[PDB]
Length: 317
Length: 317
Ligand SMILES: N[C@@H](Cc1ccc(O)cc1)C(=O)O
Ligand SMILES: N[C@@H](Cc1ccc(O)cc1)C(=O)O
Image (cartoon, rainbow over all chains, first blue to last red; front, side, top):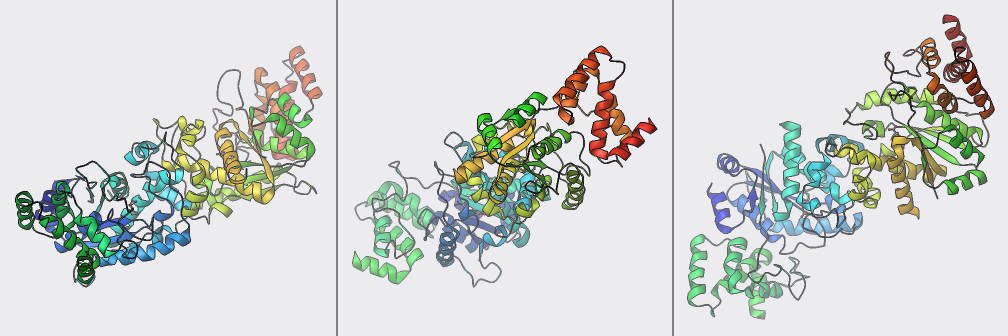
């Protein structure tokens, strides 16, 4: 209602399976929602932040978030938003990386809350022990190849080429939504822009097995210059302070272009509309001051690294 | 060489992956070959006989046959030669049916031979315990969706429709050839006409995992009238004497049309070329005698049911 209208205002709603339906439910009950994160490195990056903080916002409005670590799916690989087939990492690598990500994930959510404390879960727990026969019949019977070929993730790759491995990924994620729906009462799955197909596939699986759940995607973070958000000369802006120091993290944000700063305050910050509007006017009236830019950098560095880390960054600068 | 040339003469060779290569090998070594049979009923039928007796012929020429019972694949279902999606049978049903088929299979092969005794195997043994993750990475990485969509079995169905379940079947069979190749030295896989795609998929898997094996398909048994071989008014001609009695089995064959009889003697019998030619001339010179027709019926009933069963059939007639 207001949560959804605020998200909209901020620009965090790219698509929704049924907006009136979802608004309705959000307003009547504590909603269990989840977001998936696959270990494709030993650290999350700012590419994951919008999804992460959106979870947070759902928590603050009294909803229950589950952050899903992709122990199983990180072993297959999501073709979504990828132009090329990816290399398979080893169980050992994925296993190690999952442990870390779980750690960064925990920072942004509340586990002490009573009524809506978060849960962090690993899909290896239920995909790990599943036999192929069970999977091909219990999940696979529900999907036609024609339904799947049409998916943006796949359509985007059959000439380019795609192994059966990645083509099957959507089933796995489809299955995660069903398990979570059943064992945790999860009625909403959220994700970046590229996840629409995987989300709706989970909804198709639910619908077809139960005959009630919704999906929301966050839009791709844009730049006015038309370059790749997070694409620095430095390489990725990690959330691991040993890969990207707090000072570097802080400088990345401080260097936001005047053109982007207001979209970024709305996306990554917990500042009100009224604080954000005010900074817009100050951005207009005194743009050499860089008030919106320092506000962003302080807010986001604090979020990710905390105050002492912030304090260091500022004094180092 | 002569085995292959005889098969050819008989009309049991529809296609072969590399004829000179296969001829060569057959002539230089004892070849391990296999044929797959899926429990889709509680009995095999005359639809399976050509494949079965061809195995036999490979055994007689000194080769080693493995008859594979589809305990795992019978749980998925082969779209090959099927215009419609099939219903999934239960583990319990399939499990029960496998036990019977193993029994009928054993009748046509030699287990006492030293050097080339047969083996009967159940693919549930290695597919049963395989986890999805292992299957999607170890088998799936090797296949592009484009390779698979082109397969006659699948091409024939995407508008018609095909679940992912049946679309994946070929991987499973692909995997059987690899396991058998590795654990039994199996270098040749044979099957009916409709199996070419599944066979070549197993060859693609072998090639891509090892970088040596061949495939042979038997042609669809034809009728001069253009009707469906085995399609009786009675319903299927089973190999189970409790479903189709020896007398009925015998009558089916005795009723072979003059037009088909010589193709059937060549396909289903162990009569020489010279005996078969002779019957051709007798078919020409005295067709009301029905010499070719009784020869067929006696030969095939004996094969499937034995002499006493034959004796009954004749005296009952
Ligand atoms: N598809 C998400 C991760 C994910 C994994 C499992 C899920 O159930 C959901 C999402 C990504 O690649 O970023
Ligand atoms: N595809 C064969 C059966 C089969 C099963 C497993 C195999 O490995 C090979 C063949 C059929 O449907 O008749």
